[PDB]
Amino acid sequence: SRKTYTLTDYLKNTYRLKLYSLRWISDHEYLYKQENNILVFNAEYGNSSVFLENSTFDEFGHSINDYSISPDGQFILLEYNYVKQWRHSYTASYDIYDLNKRQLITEERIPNNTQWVTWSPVGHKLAYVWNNDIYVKIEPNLPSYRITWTGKEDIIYNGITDWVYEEEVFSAYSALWWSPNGTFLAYAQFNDTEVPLIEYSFYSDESLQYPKTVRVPYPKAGAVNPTVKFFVVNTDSLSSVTNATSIQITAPASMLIGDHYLCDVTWATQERISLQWLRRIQNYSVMDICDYDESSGRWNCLVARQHIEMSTTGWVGRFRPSEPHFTLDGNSFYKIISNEEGYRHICYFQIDKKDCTFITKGTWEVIGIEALTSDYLYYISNEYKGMPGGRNLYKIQLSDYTKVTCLSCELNPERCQYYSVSFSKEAKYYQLRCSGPGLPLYTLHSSVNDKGLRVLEDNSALDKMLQNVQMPSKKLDFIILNETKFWYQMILPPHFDKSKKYPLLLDVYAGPCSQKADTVFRLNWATYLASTENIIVASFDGRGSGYQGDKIMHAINRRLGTFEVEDQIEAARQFSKMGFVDNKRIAIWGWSYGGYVTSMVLGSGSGVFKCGIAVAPVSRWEYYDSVYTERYMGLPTPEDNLDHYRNSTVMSRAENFKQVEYLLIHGTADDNVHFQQSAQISKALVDVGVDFQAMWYTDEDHGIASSTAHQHIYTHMSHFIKQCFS
Amino acid sequence: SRKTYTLTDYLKNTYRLKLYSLRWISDHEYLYKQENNILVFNAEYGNSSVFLENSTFDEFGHSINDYSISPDGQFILLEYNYVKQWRHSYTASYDIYDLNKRQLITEERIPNNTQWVTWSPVGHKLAYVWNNDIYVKIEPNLPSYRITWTGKEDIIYNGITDWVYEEEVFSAYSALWWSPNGTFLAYAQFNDTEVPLIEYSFYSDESLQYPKTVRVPYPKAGAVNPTVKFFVVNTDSLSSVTNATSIQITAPASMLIGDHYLCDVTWATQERISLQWLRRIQNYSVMDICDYDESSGRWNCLVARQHIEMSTTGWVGRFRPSEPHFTLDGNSFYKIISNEEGYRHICYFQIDKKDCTFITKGTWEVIGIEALTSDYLYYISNEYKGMPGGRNLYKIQLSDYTKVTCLSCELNPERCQYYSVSFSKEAKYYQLRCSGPGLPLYTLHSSVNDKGLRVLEDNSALDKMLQNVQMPSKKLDFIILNETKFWYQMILPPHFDKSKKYPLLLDVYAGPCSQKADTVFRLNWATYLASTENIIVASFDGRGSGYQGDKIMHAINRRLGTFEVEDQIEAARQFSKMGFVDNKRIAIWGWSYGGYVTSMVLGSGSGVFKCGIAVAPVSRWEYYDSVYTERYMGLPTPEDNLDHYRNSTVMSRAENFKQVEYLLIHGTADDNVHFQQSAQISKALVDVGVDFQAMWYTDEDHGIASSTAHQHIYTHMSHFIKQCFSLP
Ligand SMILES: C[C@H](CCc1ccc(C(N)=O)cc1)NCC(=O)c1ccc(F)cc1
Ligand SMILES: C[C@H](CCc1ccc(C(N)=O)cc1)NCC(=O)c1ccc(F)cc1
């Protein structure tokens, strides 16, 4: 009766999860990029109007992939010729459509191959980067103003990040920040002069006779890191007669003493900017609050106005120090920091007062500050029912920290335990996005009384689609190890009979601050493996795991490849001793960090896993990037942590692979975890005489996400797993 | 009751074929390495007489890879710190040991990382190439004269070949030729300045934090080729001038008009040198004969003395124009060329006479000319019993061409049908090397009457060890294709039973002038497949194959990837119909060119093959080198042969791979068939959604001959094949 969720279903995405992506343009309205045309919705009433026809740009001559409407509403930025680079970076061509005259600006147009572009926060100003230099257009048709002249491919980056700052710290390519009203344009400058280059071959189309060598400045663990500078430009004060004057904000001295990073930049007021710096030993970070000097034109960062944030048990922040959220007058701010008990909560600061006051506390953590009004502080956390894998939106009254209200917990407890949110400009409204455990639900609410205005998408189409199929169930629970409870989840085959013994696949990530046991609803590989193959797919959040306090997360500090891999093993043993698990058919697989862990596990000699698959894994921390690696491993030097660097490689575990069936996968164009990492595992396995399976994906990167590659890799892994299990 | 030849036996080399390596030092004497002490045997009787004892090189603190004794036997060159480069090239450490004073020369030592070293043919002169420049040492202990000053890594090569010339023309790294007197040192100079670079990653050992990018001047099809120059220096005048002057030998005019290659160099006499040159369009070739003008001190090459050699049906020579063998006075020579019937035979030439006279028969071919005396000419051919896969030594009367004597045919016809030979200084004696079908057999003979003097090695040892194990047999025969018979070979499992159906594996090479069906005895992977897994391992020589005349070898001219692929398929169809072959279990596998073919076969959609394995295959000719590729495909231009270059790729047949199990394998550091070729193959398979198996070998080259990689690759392919055949 009915059918199972198949591999073809997954790969051909026959069952689509409908989302509702809206972009707020005001505090009252938002744009909804429909399928054809872009409509505008009035948050309040519910009355809609078209913003621009789907046909508007037919004969444009080019295929547009994105639109960026200025905060003015007068102009529209048209982005095309999109060419992907790293995880966030890319180059493209842009055209400016005038919504007034309804024409396409044609003079002083934006350069092809533009690296980054951004409207100012209010008018119709423009800042963009081309050839690594920054340019500014006060008005769409006026000439661009060369702000910087030092740009130089792979050497100096102005307004954009280099590889490591893109991936590991800013999580963005952009490196410019407009002041609130658009007067000032702040930017960072990266210098990779002495940073070593990673080199790999890119084969490109068949037509290319000779392979090309891709070279990108990339600091591996302990190498020379790029250096950084920060600057501020007064866009209201630049002419066409003289070059723009960039005012540099330097230091702090405690930082200039050695290698450091610029980890955060947030504007406080029209004339106040906050900068957060991080030492290379990500133990210490300092936040500076600099003000603009009127009768001097410089920016002053008064000490006494700076805040120190450190950690004695590990690094600062989950992945980096948090972002402060300033109040109206920008004289105080809120930001998530670690408790005296190791739990991350919101702390209240006065820009000139050292000791902050925690406004939340408990044995749970605030995931993020979502919106700040003079009245309430809105945030998401996992406090609800003590489930670290859940997410709910809360609002705390700033006058009385005792008055905290959960805005999502009870909306529909059965179907929703994992929320995210999108607030309007002044947080007058907000879209709640429930992504599990039931089907994704998008609703719209008004902040005044926290009333539900209307459902935006309840995925009723999918619900009618799936009632047809034999869907797997999900169990989210925990086991107790040495005083602590550790969560895990299991994707269970339909008509799960605890009387039968099911093969089990351990799906791992397990990197620092990772979470794999959650209440999110998904349609993926594991769905198919459980539904069609009758395989139980489990995940476990052990030591090093995130969102449960520092005692847990910092357990692997300076000790990667130890407790997290052991807990993964220990957890499988427990599952294997549950009765419905076929102990002779347990497998393990991981992508990225999961690939590394999956590998360390297979080479651990545990005796638990028959087989395992590792996709684009790290094999030795000295091959991975500095910023990420060093944040947990310190420096690869004898004076520091060289011994563990050398003790935690997969290759040194090669002999132990003689006991398992291993599949090793990696894209040859992986700019993140270099093919080199898997190239060294394969060689160690060969030198020690271990047979195993292998698969390279030419020209694919860490995501192996091209459509065909994606279908190919999961089809291949599927065959491996069934062979190992039948 | 009884065992077999296992995978372990192959990988661990449990059963070893004994050899007998002689190194003639005179007309009646040779040296025989006893793994510990070299001895000098007297061909006449078989005397001992140690030359260098067991432990003469202890306290040397270095492992001597090889040795080379000066012609006058007064010095011995020692080679160590070996470091492989390409297929023939390598860098090494050298030291010279004075036998007269039993001392080691410590002064003026040869530099470490020397690219090549050679004693002069007489006496003890030395010439070596270091840092791409040529050096000469008149005496081992004296300072060396630098001959050239332009050597520049990856740019200018003096006395040594660039990548393409080493691989595809000279099958050697050396590019210097001593005159038979030792008076002149001739050498080539290659310029790679404008040649594109193949670039690929080398990961090295774990310790290397950042991968290395190896860059090598390597011209792919149609790309800019390296240029060449030829010079000659008189070493006996090095001690009278100051800066030695290398006399250049240019032209031939019909060559300089465009792209060309230095083809061959052979000294005729003490002051007569012969050079063969070839056009990039390899169907035209010219030999140039130059005499040393002792007056001008130059080399005058009479244009009237030039010899053209061309082909109307294909390229020239098997892989290149053949080598000339000059008579004692240099006024005449013997050279193998294909006759009007398309069969390669020997013809006699006079330096002053463009028309040559053929001295050997018809429907078979002379493999090579082995020796020349005033009396007879010795050569090897496959004329015996009309088996193109056999090899015998014959001698023909120079004064009467109808007097031809086979010297090895009947020595032991049942055990020996594949011979190679090694004559002494004046061909007064010669060693015969029987390679199959029976266990190798080495014997010494004397040329006066071709009388067998004695058996040098008969492998009686291996023989004993094998009578206890179930060894496979080898069927060598032919099938018929379009009125013409083509040979094949089959490695049959023990106690073969024609009634049972055996799975079959087609082992293919099938490149231009290839031969996979022969009378050679081998202990390889196929031995194990047959002896242990009971798999019939066959090889077929179809159109394009060699040693059977141009009609067959030139059939795929300008048409690579067509008939040769088809024939491989047609042969399997015939094998499947044979009755003792299991129709549903026929696999195919090949390495190199055979990888290309295997991949082309699997992508043909003939439905004949269940699975296949391609190791380091070519995927499209534009990716391969110019010299080898263009020789058979012409240039990749619309004016020439671009259309077939595009119609003969593996990728364009990706879709058909859906009906077969394919194992693609390749070394990441393959400087010959770049990893790129397989990288493009997998991408095309991924793009059409076909699943396959893959395996890359880190830092391994085209030979994947690393001890561990070798064991690992064969181990990997065994699992794949017996899995495809449902063994185990
Ligand atoms: C920007 C990202 C964010 C952190 C992150 C996210 C997801 C995984 C994850 N799913 O494993 C691992 C680590 N870091 C670099 C990265 O992608 C990475 C780190 C470590 C590694 F072994 C592979 C890749
Ligand atoms: C120096 C060699 C000598 C001729 C040769 C020998 C063996 C094979 C053979 N076993 O396939 C193919 C060709 N040619 C270049 C070469 O290595 C080559 C040619 C074509 C190809 F597809 C791969 C490699």
Image (cartoon, coloured by chain):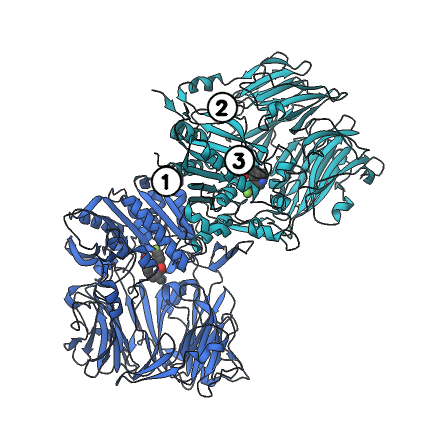
Chain colours: A blue, B cyan
Q: Where residue B32 appears, x then y in whole percent?
A: 57, 20
- Mark 3 Cα shell of 10 Å, populated few (<14), some (14-19), many (≥20): some
Subunit under mark 1 = A
Identify the image quadrant of the N terminus of chain A: bottom left
Q: Secondary structure at mark 2?
A: loop
Picture disc at residue B81: 3
Query: What residue lies at 55% left-to-right and 53% top-to-bottom?
Result: A210
| Mark 3 → mark 2, Cα distance in angstroms | 27 Å
Looking at the rendered structure, the kind of residue marked 1 is Asp
Residue B458 on image: x %, y % = 52, 17
Report the side of A645 relative to B344 (left or right): left
B217 in relation to A384, above or below: above
Q: Which residue is mark 1?
A: A691
Dot 3 or dot 2: first in sequence order is 2
Q: Residue at x 19, y 56 (%)?
A: A486
Q: Which amino acid, by three-letter code, is at mark 2?
A: Leu
Which quadrant of the view contains residue B552?
Answer: top right
Check the image and report above or below for B667 versus B368.
Answer: below
The reply to whether residue B273 is in sight is yes
Tag in front: 3 or 1: 1
Q: Is mark 1 within 8 Å of ligand 2?
A: no
The picture quadrant where one finds residue B510 is: top right
Residue B472 in the image: state x and y as whole percent. Answer: 44, 25
- Give the crowd class for mark 1: few <14, some 14-19, many >=20 residues within 10 Å: many
Which residue bears the numbered disc 2? B17
